[PDB]
Image (spheres, rainbow, N blue to C red):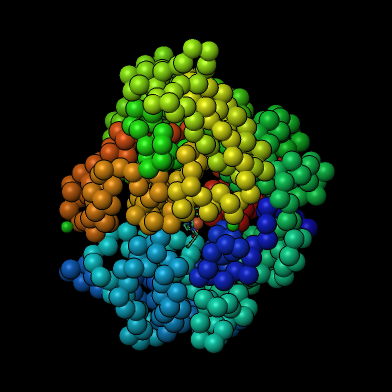
Length: 498
Ligand SMILES: O=C(O)CN(CCN(CC(=O)O)Cc1ccccc1O)Cc1ccccc1
Ligand SMILES: [Cl-]
Ligand SMILES: [Cl-]
Ligand SMILES: [Fe+3]
């Protein structure tokens, strides 16, 4: 079975509704469904299902010329009518897509002919093409598979145009994909991919050592990092670690005592020994982060000043703000109140817990009492949406989302970043500038607005950046070098070539 592989994922791929979110998995939606335009590593898009496009002078009306040779995997044609019908299906559920500003920008979509698709926007939104390139929601399912002329209430078969077809799924067991033998583009070398559902990282590593699976591919949570390092020395296996793809950080609640105080947030940003954290909890496998976005992120090379590990300075900042230590005690107090902060995280995530214990210890050394609140996922998501946290673990979203889409979403009240920022006097100005930057085509003004937003978020110490994390791979050697997709959340199975 040289052209069949077995891999794993912590959950099933879901129903593969192209227009909905969890329990659908972004990498599996991208295996079956395709965009008008495809994201590239240099930050551009190339023609995909749209072979070319034009736009009006005011940048609000766009017209795409679609390929005329593409079929859905069930034989039905892909054309401008089918594409228009998918946009209607997505936007009939608009409210759900509020995080993604293109969904509020699209005013009209219509098929002018079988090959001409016209999209009209509210404003000259600059990230238009990059948001059409995302895994969801602007993909394409055969309209025959709508339920009652819609997708927001479910689909029939998950029929896309892409290079893989879902063969079958068994909840809590496995998902099987096969190559689309009528694909309009390049045939994948691999014919069949089985996903074993294996939620625990330790069990994933055991499945690979026993040879039950051929490939693990994921972020820093993929398997235990000590095990990963050991596998990278084991000549029977192959391992890889990409260049960093996004940031992991704490979000600090500027609207909740005592993180509502700038001096407290500044002191916390000097309290953590990040290098030690990464060598201790992560096994030396990741990068230290000093700012929300790494300097290599577009529009984020700003010369922002790092807060290096400096307990002396953290203590001095707290002392100056009136948080001093009472005879007998190791925890500071101001106005009778102890310097106590709750750090919420997913209680069953061993790596998260690991990091939280380190953060609690480092902060105790400067006289902050961090209480760890480890809870199930739904509970932590609820806290993020509603600002019920002191500090929370968080992360950015990688290319092509960083920085524009991650910033865009800071305006949405049901997101952790809005909630963390809600206490800032300049929050309204930041949100107004985020709206401006997304529609600004004066390149000078666009860079100025990104520098201002990112600078204010850095100076206000809203985040405690921890690490810039990478994608990791463990594979049987016979699979060869495993590529990495331009979009951080996709897996390029079509590029694997034993
Ligand atoms: O991740 C979130 O904060 C929420 N999601 C929206 C934003 N995410 C992109 C995506 O999921 O397609 C960001 C995102 C980017 C990169 C990897 C994973 C991601 O989840 C899901 C959701 C949508 C509507 C209402 C509630 C939740
Ligand atoms: Cl999920
Ligand atoms: Cl402009
Ligand atoms: Fe999401």
